[PDB]
Amino acid sequence: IVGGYTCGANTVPYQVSLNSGYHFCGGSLINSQWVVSAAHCYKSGIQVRLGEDNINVVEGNEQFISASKSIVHPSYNSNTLNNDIMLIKLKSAASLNSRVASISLPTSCASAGTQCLISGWGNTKSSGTSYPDVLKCLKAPILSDSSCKSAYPGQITSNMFCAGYLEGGKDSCQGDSGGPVVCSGKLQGIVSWGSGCAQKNKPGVYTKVCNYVSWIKQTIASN
Ligand SMILES: N=C(N)c1ccc(/N=N/Nc2ccc(C(=N)N)cc2)cc1
Ligand SMILES: [Ca+2]
């Protein structure tokens, strides 16, 4: 997260770190056994780390639970990042309390202008590289589809939305991928892609979760 702020330990209780020896992507816990992340975060041997703040220090609220299965969206296209969503099932149910909590799926798509919270342990620099150890947060509005499409001609599908700031300076970034965009207490987005980070007229592009709720629910129901 570039231009964000330190969330505060366990203030984003649904935020998970996907760990394969190191943090490589975010995710969002959507029930005790399931995490939603970006399909481009797919890899085998994922350990889901819940209850994280400092991902480099055991601070006492962590739950580390290996994935038992990952399900990449049936229509995920890695070239276009269309349908950049994947479900990860935990081998065991996370223990849910205030510091580790699922985030509600949307019942409706959020509109442009809705303020959201984007979070992650990704790079905090738009130029160069610095990875935070504690969870970073960014309040960012969903941008209009028109501004999104204008920013990224020929790339924004109906399964994507832009959020952030056209002026740049504030954005998610590498290492935030897969993580949440939560708006009014609903998971509306998944950190998906963008050109660089926090670049002018290159806002973050997010998987439009509301399109996937049916798939998520039915997948969970049968897996
Ligand atoms: N909001 C942003 N600017 C932004 C946020 C996260 C981000 N990270 N994406 N990283 C990323 C890495 C690999 C792939 C792939 N295998 N195709 C896709 C995306 C890139 C840009
Ligand atoms: Ca930790």
Image (tube, rainbow, N blue to C red):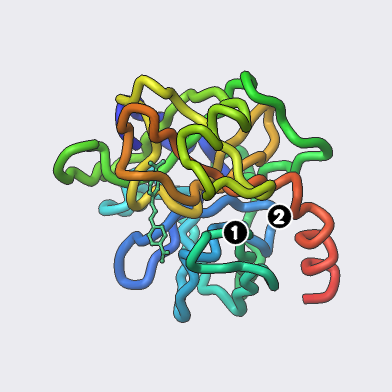
Disc 2 secondary structure class = strand
Residue at x 50% of width, y 25% of height: 140
Question: What is the x, y in percent for residue 154?
Answer: 53, 48
- Sequence-wise, which precedes: disc 1 or disc 2? 2
**Distance from Cα at disc 1 to Cα at disc 2:** 24 Å
Residue at x 78% of width, y 52% of height: 213
Residue at x 59% of width, y 39% of height: 161
In front: 148, or 133? 148
In the image, residue 155 sits, relative to residue 48, either above or below, namely above
Image quarter in which the N terminus is found: top left
In front: 90, or 24? 24
Left or right relative to 204: residue 24: left
* Residue 100 seen in render: no
In the image, residue 108 sits, relative to residue 179, either above or below, namely above
Q: Residues within 10 Å of mark 2 (few under 14, many from 20)?
A: many
In the image, residue 212 sits, relative to residue 218, either above or below, namely above
The residue that label 2 is drawn on is: 31
Residue at x 37% of width, y 72% of height: 20
Left or right relative to 123: residue 11: right
The residue that label 1 is drawn on is: 82
Q: Residues within 10 Å of mark 1 (few under 14, many from 20)?
A: many
Question: What is the x, y in percent for residue 158?
Answer: 69, 47
Image quarter in which the C terminus is found: bottom right
Residue lying farthest to the front in this orientation? 154
